[PDB]
Image (cartoon, coloured by chain):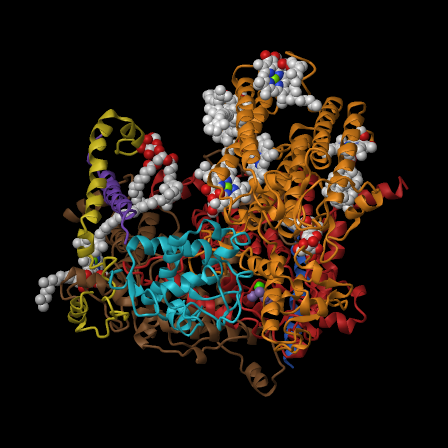
Chain colours: A cyan, B purple, C yellow, D red, E brown, F blue, G orange
Amino acid sequence: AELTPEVLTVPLNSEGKTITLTEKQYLEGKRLFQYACASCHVGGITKTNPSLDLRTETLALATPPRDNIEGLVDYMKNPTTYDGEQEIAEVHPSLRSADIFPKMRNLTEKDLVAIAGHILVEPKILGDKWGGGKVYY
Amino acid sequence: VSYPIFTVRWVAVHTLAVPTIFFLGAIAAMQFIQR
Amino acid sequence: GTTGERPFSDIITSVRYWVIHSITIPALFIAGWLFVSTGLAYDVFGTPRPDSYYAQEQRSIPLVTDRFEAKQQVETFLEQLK
Amino acid sequence: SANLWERFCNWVTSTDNRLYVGWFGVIMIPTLLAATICFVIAFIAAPPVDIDGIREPVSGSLLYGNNIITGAVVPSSNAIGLHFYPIWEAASLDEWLYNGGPYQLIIFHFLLGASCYMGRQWELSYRLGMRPWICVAYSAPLASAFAVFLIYPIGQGSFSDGMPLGISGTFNFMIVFQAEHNILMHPFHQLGVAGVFGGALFCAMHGSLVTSSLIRETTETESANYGYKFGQEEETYNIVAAHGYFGRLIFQYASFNNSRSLHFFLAAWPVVGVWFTALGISTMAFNLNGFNFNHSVIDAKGNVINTWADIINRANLGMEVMHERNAHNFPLDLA
Amino acid sequence: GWFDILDDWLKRDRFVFVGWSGILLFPCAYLALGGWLTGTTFVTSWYTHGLASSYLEGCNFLTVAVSTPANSMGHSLLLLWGPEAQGDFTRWCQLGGLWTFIALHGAFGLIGFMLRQFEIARLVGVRPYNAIAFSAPIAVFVSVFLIYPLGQSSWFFAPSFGVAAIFRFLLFFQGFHNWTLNPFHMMGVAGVLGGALLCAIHGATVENTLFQDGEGASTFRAFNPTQAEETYSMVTANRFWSQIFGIAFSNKRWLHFFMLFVPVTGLWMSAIGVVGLALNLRSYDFISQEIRAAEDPEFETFYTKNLLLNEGIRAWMAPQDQPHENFVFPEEVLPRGNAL
Amino acid sequence: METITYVFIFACIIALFFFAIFFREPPRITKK
Amino acid sequence: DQESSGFAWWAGNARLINLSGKLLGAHVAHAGLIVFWAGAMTLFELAHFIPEKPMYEQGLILIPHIATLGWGVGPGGEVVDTFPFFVVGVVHLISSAVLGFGGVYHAIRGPETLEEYSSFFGYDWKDKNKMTTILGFHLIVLGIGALLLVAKAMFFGGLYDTWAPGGGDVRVITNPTLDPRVIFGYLLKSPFGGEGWIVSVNNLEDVVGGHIWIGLICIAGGIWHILTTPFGWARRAFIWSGEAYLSYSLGALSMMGFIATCFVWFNNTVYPSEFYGPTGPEASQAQAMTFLIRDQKLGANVGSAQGPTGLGKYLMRSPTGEIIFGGETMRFWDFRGPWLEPLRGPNGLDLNKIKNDIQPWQERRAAEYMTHAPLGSLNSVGGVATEINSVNFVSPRSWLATSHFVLAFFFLVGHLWHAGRARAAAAGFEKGIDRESEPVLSMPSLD
Ligand code: CLA
Ligand code: CLA
Ligand code: CLA
Ligand code: CLA
Ligand code: CLA
Ligand code: CLA
Ligand SMILES: CC1=C(/C=C/C(C)=C/C=C/C(C)=C/C=C/C=C(C)/C=C/C=C(C)/C=C/C2=C(C)CCCC2(C)C)C(C)(C)CCC1
Ligand SMILES: CC1=C(/C=C/C(C)=C/C=C/C(C)=C/C=C/C=C(C)/C=C/C=C(C)/C=C/C2=C(C)CCCC2(C)C)C(C)(C)CCC1
Ligand SMILES: CC1=C(\C=C/C(C)=C/C=C/C(C)=C/C=C/C=C(C)/C=C/C=C(C)/C=C/C2=C(C)CCCC2(C)C)C(C)(C)CCC1
């Protein structure tokens, strides 16, 4: 019962190719997740819009697919609506709006990848907990 | 006065004192365990 | 207002006491420390190590379900690398 | 007449009154009388009150289907919040009783009177040449009423969230409080029960020790109480025999031999403990809640290993999730 | 005779009085406190409650506990050498053997302790009203930690020895027994709360009605340890409360017995209520209320409100609080208000 | 019927309060 | 000099009631502790301070105090230069050494009494002239201090105005409200819902203006006391002793401690939500805003939306008819804030502005404040008691309010304690009832 590199193996892109994170990245991602996400996305939910969570399945049915490092990283730069037919960086933290969301100024591409990996790793560990809310607490 | 050393009070005192410090040392070590 | 025992105040003040207890008190401390740090404690009380609550995949709890064959059932729980 | 007003002041301040109406009494007596009269009438005959301001009246009076245990005086509407709502602020009494008008009239009058009651407990002590601080002990139960009836509503932003005036209603206040604040896991509360448990403990301690060490002056078939006369010179119990016993129960130096050091401790412990429990409610009135150890201890992989703290949280959710059914429209309870 | 010589030694006035009682008290009392402090730091509750309960696992002073045995155990005494543990010590800990250890030992320790009160009092030649009083704490421990679970399915539903583990015991009784609505419990708190009042009010009364027996302001030194005159004005105390409260004591012997009666009687009433909860004979509902609430959907009291809170507590807590039941409650079956 | 019973006992306690305060036994000093 | 034959050890400081010299040392050494904390804590805060991050998310209570005075901040509370924070911190910490020096000096070296080593500084508690005079001195010192604020605001830079026309920014106040009808009007305001008494101040003009009045009035009373003595009634009413004067100031601080608690909890102006957290109501108001904004974007007509109770999911009416936010947030319809006001009309929240004048900066403002409500645990876990560990946060508004209520209360206890003793000390029975002449025994039996 431990955090194996087997668990830290998450899909990198849409074309099946995967990437293996390290215990350093995970922790770093988890920390960065608290720094800039937890505020609204604590435990995989979304306080300011409970209809959309960070479940891998939910990210998969997103448009474009956001259930991989590449999907998530792009989002953190130019976030869109679930159908992708509208850019929402003005009311959502991102690199192209770091002037508006100062927390995103420090964040560099390493940080983005770490954060992305965290979102994909947690449900591997927590399971239904990561997606659901108080019901699973 | 010529007080003795080993007494019933001494026994009582140690039954609590000796394990305590042994526990305080053990717990103190627990503060460094992780994952 | 007095009994046979040697007044604490005198003993806690006596140099002889500290000559003794500067050795004894830290000794017990280091011993208790070793008791945990060497992982012995884990085995004396069957307490699970951070990597010994579940199996890798399993997410179920090793709940004891019958009194008489409990000990045997517990041992079986340790089998699945738990 | 030596001077009407001069006589008046002499009558008020008079220590020859059956009940000492003090200067604080001049405020207490009317206020306490208004509070009690309104309460009694309300508790019996008041119509249902829309406490949560959601047009969902809660009946808490006897004549409207309640008994002693369930009956209560329902807090003012959540539509009023912290607004001042006297009778002359309503188009009619019908409206006034619907929006929980009586409640404010009672709590304000009570808290006012109960404060002057503390003020009077000094005055009489002053008039009788005895030391003060008796009122200081009463400051503890008063500060709780204040925390429960005034401080928490102020903090939460509505008098509708103040503790109701009733048995079961008091139970609701607690259960919900536990949900929103996790009070059992708060140091100030824990100090409160400690003072309260310790209090009852020490009350039994002192009580027993003294009554057990009484000097014999009574017959075998005569009340042991008669062995005391009101206005004695000497003591009625052997405090030296008391100390001898209790000193052997534990050990000598862990026993009192000074009656004055004894009674101070008897007074200090519960008062201080309740003082913190009152500060607890007053602190959690600004949402500085108890310890949150939810999902603290986790295993090497990241799995959540539950504690009793987690089992507590499950009970708490149930309270949270079910309380005020139809009052919430949005995800977070920030009110 | 060796007996009277054995007696001689035991009843010798030491720093820590032993006595005949001590032969029972000290062994149990120590093992009970020791067993707790042991389990508190080392032994787990994983195989029994699916819980971490020790410092070794990461619990703190509040969340640590010596949890009850499994529900499988039933009311088994769980002897170290019993059919369950089979002499094994490690297994014994994991099956929650330390709970029945602490319980039974502590039980006899409370027996030994009251006996100590009885024995010492006899020697000192004082009345045993300290032993009579200590009966209330006995009744509570007996009713709660023994009688109650003896009425339930197993020791599992007894209060586990620990801070937080007791808090759940409170919430449980609320959710499941509606314990606050019980007349016997109410008498309980009235005694404790009323007892904590007597404690406060009497001490303060005394400290502020004292005579001047010294020239210093710190009047503590000015007390005569060798009886004589009353250190405080009972007569002044009387007239005070008679004018501020209307009623006042005037018989120290009654005042102090009253201080014994109130908190002892309360604890005893609360015991009886718990004895009734063992068979689940609770004070859960008011039939007249429910009948109207059923026919009339607009009838609402603070009583009805509370029951809904109970429904939530039961539903959301039962799964992880009663593992042995393998409870599975779908999200849709979970009772919930709006939004929350 | 229930309402009456509740108020009755209550009214009785208040009545007792009165007598307890103003019709007590006069607390006499020394020579008692 | 002083030992057990005066007071007990645990009442040690009461042995200094009549030792002017040493009693001055205490006050000078004590005042150093206050300056020391202020200094050492500011540097502690700065040392942890993260510029590109909200102050309320960093456990700051001193740097946001400096920020309000227009220092190191700019547009929208953006931190520009951390040097002023560093300065305020270090200067204090230095001054603590100077004060601490004198304190220690007067307490163990200098004259144990002052009366002889200087009749000007020496004093007598019962000397109604010296007391009113020393009081007169401090009444001026505080008066100038009140003007020190007025100066910083009108001349030396200004203050942080959240109500800034172009959006929260440091603004120089050059038009202080000096109209007495307006200023002292606040004192005649109710302390309940709506009419908020002193805490209801909502613009820097009044703040600066009011301080001008206080500054002058204080010094005016400062001079008055120098050149006078207490009247007749003033003497026949009060108790004149060292403890009595203490009690009077104790209840005074208690009252101010309670007023400060409500100020940091309710007021938006002198406690900017940009530096501190959002106020309690502000946070609950934001959630209604947020989800009114969301659902409306989903095509919902918020104006006519009917909630479970049939009251109005998003918008409803106040008891006086004003259009307000719906839900449990109906209790906070008294909230006013820069982000929300442009949506308000003459009858409350305007359905047309709500329908198409919602600005993006407002949406994310609502989301921010919504997700930063002053809800948390003692171990600092942001959210409801049932929340999960992740977000380590507790609103500064929560820390300050709770801390200062505890202090204010205990000071009310201290007041009663020292006021009760002074009355008994004066009349002379604070040490017990006279065994011989027992007062009660001379009064008729009420029986
Ligand atoms: C006098 C003090 C005292 C008392 C009353 C108890 C009481 C108890 N202990 Mg205990 N204990 C003590 C001191 C004491 N302990 C000390 C000092 C230690 C440290 C070594 C322990 C260590 C300890 C452990 C490790 C355990 C207990 C347990 C128990 C419980 C069950 C034991 C049992 O079955 O008794 C048996 C009773 C007797 C043996 C009394 C027999 C007396 C008769 C007169 C003698 C006859 C013998 C003769 C051969 C019979 C012939 C008959 C013929 C037909 C064969 C019981 C509540 C168990 C427990 O709590 O389970 C949950 C447990 O596992 N104790
Ligand atoms: C302006 C504030 C002020 C001032 C100048 C005084 C001054 C005085 N008080 Mg006093 N008092 C105050 C506020 C104040 N008080 C308040 C607010 C209360 C309410 C609690 C009291 C309650 C009080 C009592 C009950 C008594 C005094 C007494 C006295 C006199 C002797 C001083 C003494 O006993 O020191 C001795 C100081 C101590 C023993 C220190 C106590 C430590 C406190 C209780 C703990 C604080 C907790 C701390 C924050 C936690 C730190 C963590 C720790 C691990 C480091 C002296 C004239 C005594 C006297 O003679 O009356 C005239 C006396 O009996 N006061
Ligand atoms: C704000 C805290 C404070 C302050 C300023 C004082 C101040 C004072 N107390 Mg005091 N006291 C306090 C808290 C405080 N107390 C508390 C909490 C208690 C309860 C435990 C007491 C109990 C108490 C008793 C029982 C007595 C005093 C007395 C005194 C006075 C004489 C001090 C003395 O005997 O020197 C002795 C000095 C020393 C033994 C050396 C101490 C070292 C110095 C003072 C500290 C150095 C500070 C710093 C590290 C150096 C900086 C140097 C730098 C500037 C260069 C003095 C005015 C006495 C009195 O009445 O005066 C006649 C007295 O009898 N106090
Ligand atoms: C009273 C004003 C006050 C306020 C509002 C704050 C507020 C804050 N401080 Mg702070 N602080 C203060 C005074 C204050 N402090 C003082 C006087 C000191 C000097 C010791 C410090 C030293 C300090 C440090 C070193 C740090 C803070 C930090 C913080 C922040 C995090 C709070 C936290 O986690 O504390 C939680 C604290 C507790 C839960 C302890 C509560 C203790 C209570 C009051 C004890 C009560 C028991 C009672 C007195 C017993 C007596 C009874 C007996 C007589 C019978 C917060 C903004 C931290 C920070 O900025 O990081 C973000 C940080 O690292 N503060
Ligand atoms: C609460 C403040 C305070 C008060 C009332 C006193 C009072 C006193 N001190 Mg003293 N002192 C203090 C703080 C204080 N000190 C501090 C902080 C220190 C550390 C540096 C000292 C160090 C000190 C020493 C070393 C000595 C005294 C002495 C004395 C006594 C003789 C008067 C004197 O020296 O003034 C003479 C000086 C003046 C009258 C003029 C001083 C004016 C200064 C330079 C300007 C101050 C500006 C001020 C901060 C702003 C106010 C202006 C504002 C209204 C606009 C007198 C009782 C002496 C003593 O014990 O003799 C009995 C002595 O030898 N003090
Ligand atoms: C904090 C600073 C301070 C202090 C401690 C004092 C202290 C004193 N002043 Mg004073 N004064 C001050 C500042 C201060 N002054 C200032 C700044 C001015 C200029 C305006 C004056 C002008 C002044 C005059 C003209 C007189 C005094 C007098 C007095 C003495 C008697 C006060 C009295 O009996 O009031 C007791 C008050 C009452 C009996 C009235 C109670 C009714 C109050 C005001 C309303 C209820 C309060 C309520 C709870 C608070 C709510 C707020 C309200 C706005 C709603 C006393 C020594 C008198 C004296 O003896 O002259 C030397 C006197 O005639 N003062
Ligand atoms: C089980 C068992 C047993 C037993 C054993 C024992 C008996 C042990 C003991 C043990 C012990 C005997 C331990 C102890 C411990 C203790 C501790 C661990 C403590 C701690 C403490 C602390 C931590 C403190 C704290 C505090 C307080 C509380 C006060 C205030 C302040 C302070 C903080 C200081 C036997 C073998 C017989 C058999 C088998 C079973
Ligand atoms: C507007 C404003 C302002 C201002 C304010 C002011 C101006 C205030 C004032 C205030 C005041 C001006 C107050 C006063 C107070 C008073 C008092 C508090 C008093 C008290 C008194 C007493 C307490 C007394 C008592 C008594 C009696 C009555 C009888 C006889 C005896 C005795 C003495 C006990 C500010 C700045 C904030 C800001 C802006 C806004
Ligand atoms: C009387 C008395 C007392 C009290 C005392 C006191 C209260 C004292 C105070 C003292 C004080 C009040 C002190 C102060 C100090 C301060 C200082 C000494 C300062 C320092 C500074 C510096 C050193 C600088 C600089 C810096 C910076 C700028 C940054 C970097 C870091 C540093 C920090 C280096 C007692 C209770 C004990 C006992 C009895 C007697």
Q: Relative to residue E104, is residue A132 depicted above or below?
A: below
Please identify the quadrant where the N terminus of chain D is shown.
top right
Query: From where the camera sits, is residue C41 visible?
Result: yes
Which residue extends farthest bottom? E295
Q: Name the foreground residue: E12 vs D318.
A: D318
Query: Where is residue G41 drawn, in percent x and y?
Result: 51, 36
Residue at 27 percent across and 62 percent down: it is E99
User: As drawn, is G45 to the left or to the right of A108?
Assistant: right
Q: Relative to residue G240, is residue D219 depicted above or below?
A: below
Query: From where the camera sits, is residue D235 visible?
Result: no
Residue at 15 percent across and 68 percent down: it is C79
Q: Name the foreground residue: G1 vs A46.
A: A46
Q: Name the foreground residue: G50 vs E289.
A: G50
Query: Where is residue E98 drawn, in percent x and y?
Result: 25, 60
User: As drawn, is E38 to the left or to the right of A51?
Assistant: left
Please identify the quadrant where the C terminus of chain D is shown.
bottom right
Which residue extends farthest right? D1
User: As drawn, is G79 to the left or to the right of E280?
Assistant: right
Query: Where is residue D246 drawn, in percent x and y?
Result: 38, 45
- Location of ligand 8 given as a quarter of the image: top right
Q: Quadrant of residue A1?
A: bottom left
Q: Name the foreground residue: D149 vs A45.
A: A45
